[PDB]
DNA sequence: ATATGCTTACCGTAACTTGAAAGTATTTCGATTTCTTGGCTTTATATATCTTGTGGAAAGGACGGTGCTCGCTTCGGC
């Protein structure tokens, strides 16, 4: 069975109280009868730390270097930017050249 | 001399969009299975008759260390 949007709060609370070291004990103390890998995916999907914030200037240098080094025609491989630049997903990163 | 007036660069998530990797049903090629006939094995006295294959004969060609001292021959003597 899927979640009911009521266990992620206690999950992140226990993860912050323990230090995000061992997710197995966290899942066992949470009492969901599910594997740690099955709940960690939804935890990271509901987490906000995976995203980014207002754009700086020093990262523009790296983006321009990566473009001038591995861009082809009118297509830009933003997946390479996701691989190199941490924090940027594939959805909202394309705006960096839109 | 400055705040709200409207105007627009842009960093908040979202879905219907183009096409390559990955799971799914389907008929076709080929390999497998199952039928068919028919001889294998016993017997029966019959017995035909003509050839086959043999066999003990005839008869052949085929290959089956070192003195040591009698005596044998050949010249060879005067």
Image (cartoon, rainbow, N blue to C red):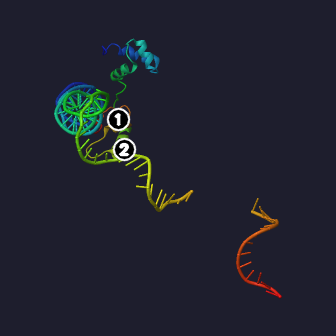
Q: Is residue B61 above or below residue A71?
A: below
Front residue of this view, candidates B40 and A1? B40
Q: How many marks?
A: 2
**Residue drawn at (43%, 19%) of the image:** A23
Q: Residue at x 45, y 16 (%)?
A: A25
Tell me how far mark 2 sits from mark 1, CA to CA: 14 Å
Mark 2 falls on what kind of element? helix
Q: Position of residue B1 (x, y in %)?
A: 28, 31
Q: Quadrant of residue A77?
A: top left
Q: Position of residue B44 (x, y in %)?
A: 27, 28
Q: Residue A15's spot in the image, x, y percent?
A: 42, 18
Q: Is residue B50 left or right of residue B78?
A: left
Q: Which residue is mark 2?
A: A65
* As drawn, B63 above or below A78: below
A84 vs B47, left or right, is right
Q: Nearer the viewer, mark 2 or mark 1?
A: 1
| Quadrant of the drawing holding the C terminus of chain A | top left
Where residue A89 sits: x, y (%)? Answer: 32, 31
């Amino acid at each position: 069975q899927e979640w009911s949007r009521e266990e992620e709060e206690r999950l992140q609370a226990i993860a912050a109280a323990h230090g995000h070291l061992e997710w197995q004990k966290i899942a066992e103390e949470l009492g969901t009868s599910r594997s740690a890998f099955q709940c960690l995916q939804k935890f990271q999907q509901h987490n906000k730390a995976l995203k980014r914030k207002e754009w700086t200037e020093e990262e523009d240098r790296m983006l321009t270097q990566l473009v001038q080094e591995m861009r082809v025609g009118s297509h830009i491989p933003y997946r390479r930017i996701v691989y190199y630049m941490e924090g940027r997903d594939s959805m909202q990163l394309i705006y960096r050249w839109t």
